[PDB]
Image 1 (cartoon, protein in one colour):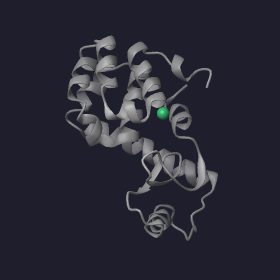
Image 2 (cartoon, protein in one colour):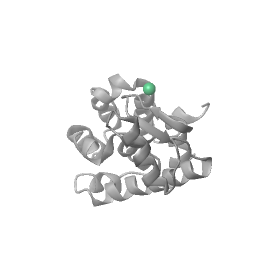
Image 3 (cartoon, protein in one colour):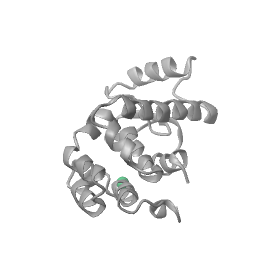
Amino acid sequence: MNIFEMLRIDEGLRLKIYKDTEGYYTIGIGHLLTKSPSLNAAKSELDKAIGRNTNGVITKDEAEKLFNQDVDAAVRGILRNAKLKPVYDSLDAVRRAAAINMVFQMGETGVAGFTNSLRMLQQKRWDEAAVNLAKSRWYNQTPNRAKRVITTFRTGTWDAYKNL
Ligand SMILES: [Cl-]
């Protein structure tokens, strides 16, 4: 297991524009197009992202290209953020994947708001962080996904993603 397989499990793959769990226009492997409620806005963003007149449909190769760029962007956002870098740097490789997952889903600013949970992660208080992380809009809105990520922070293993 690695970060790409993990997110592919959590986001799926759809080759036509769809709405994500919050109602926003999305494509591929969780690539957010726009928060605007206009489908025309979303098709404009898609065509700009891909570089061609797509008419709301992309290929599997195009989806995996956006995915590679989004994973790279999530990692670089972590390493540039002063609140996130020291936590990431303190973690083992499996738990680092959990941190990238959260940044991919909710963005760098959103994760840096989990101030208490980040401190507990840095101190390697795993059971305590896991409790604090579940006291969140994130957990109540997407509880199966949040459970898998939290389990990964708590155990440092991939057990939540095996079987799936
Ligand atoms: Cl969920």
